[PDB]
Image (cartoon, rainbow, N blue to C red):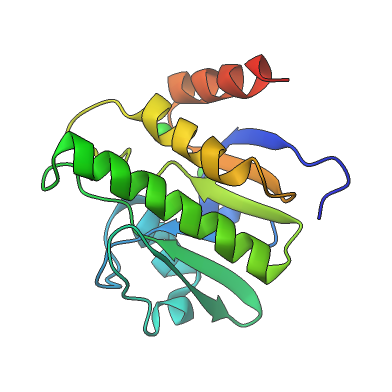
Length: 163
Ligand SMILES: [Cl-]
Ligand SMILES: [Cl-]
Ligand SMILES: [Cl-]
């Protein structure tokens, strides 16, 4: 584990991360997809061999020795707010189990269900709070990746408020 486990946020492409493993915002079918998923497919295509997994779960596939944890958040266009909230919390709990099993000291993670699976709603606080609920009991350094300048400021404020 990290000596003083922390949370950080960076505004840049997660495919350029400086962590020991990455979480992909995957689709259930293991397809190249869009957004984060397409960037992950271009950087670590080998990790999409048998990466299909249900909504609410995470499945890790190695690219060489680098782990790619495919975490499938719900598409809020298809799920109700209640059931989607439950599946989003579940996907993050599965990411925490995989990060612990892998023994990594750091992990790069995007906010699940905040892009094309958001159903057109701003889900920064919802998704980030479920990330904290799952990752707080782990001792890996967590680095959250985002692309919007206002989201970077809001995620940074939420991290600092708890310290
Ligand atoms: Cl970039
Ligand atoms: Cl998304
Ligand atoms: Cl963003």
